Length: 129
Ligand SMILES: [Cl-]
Ligand SMILES: [Cl-]
Ligand SMILES: [Cl-]
Ligand SMILES: [Cl-]
Ligand SMILES: [Cl-]
Ligand SMILES: [Cl-]
Ligand SMILES: [Cl-]
Ligand SMILES: [Cl-]
Ligand code: NA
Image (tube, rainbow, N blue to C red; front, side, top):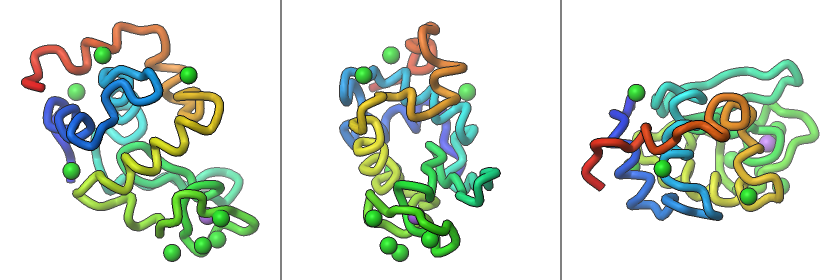
């Protein structure tokens, strides 16, 4: 599924991501925008052989099992395929663990490079939330 901007903001809020670990909803929408263009089916292979999955491009290196990332962990205890669902629950639950891991949303390099310190409120502006 390709989410609308306000549609995704509303799902993220429903799943308790708005201000999770102090990160406003705008931050999560911004990160999803640049990670996946809001497309739940986004996959991208990394140079190291790991793969990023879903709206927030969660990496098989640590967070999900895809059976093809040697020496990797599955800290969210999910198949990476669960992260491609039109239902964002698994992505949201796993992102909660990732953002709690010590570096906050810096875990998402695109968030650091494209969202951090910007007017992230723009990403939820006009949305009925
Ligand atoms: Cl947009
Ligand atoms: Cl915001
Ligand atoms: Cl596993
Ligand atoms: Cl693996
Ligand atoms: Cl593991
Ligand atoms: Cl699995
Ligand atoms: Cl959903
Ligand atoms: Cl933080
Ligand atoms: Na893995």
